[PDB]
Length: 51
Length: 51
Image (cartoon, rainbow over all chains, first blue to last red; front, side, top):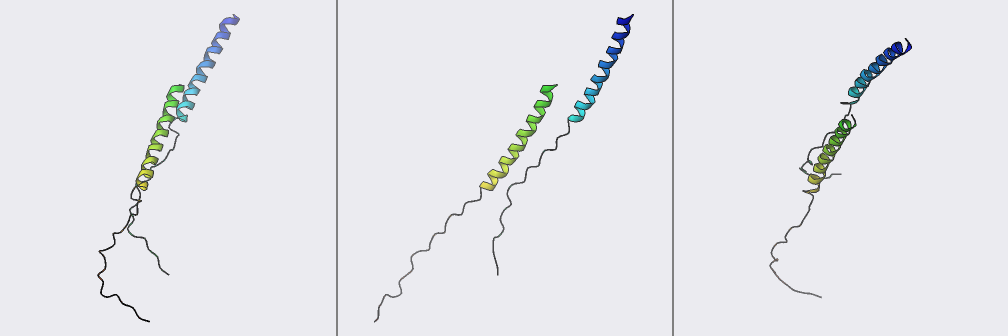
């Protein structure tokens, strides 16, 4: 009755690993920060200097 | 699930570069000095000489 018991334990193992892959994949996603785009250059109201 | 993750990273990359192009373009503009136009010739009140 060896084959019958062997097959059962193998089925359970592969199911458990697949579900674990899902959690890891989805957690991996939506895990990217990125950047902001600086606005257009600031208009120059004045440039001057003093002592 | 390779294609799904690949596409996502590519989308983010192109967005970031486009925003960077904008800042650079606008900063490039309004960055031209130019010149002034000298007034009309000065009227001659006198021309003379001494020792």
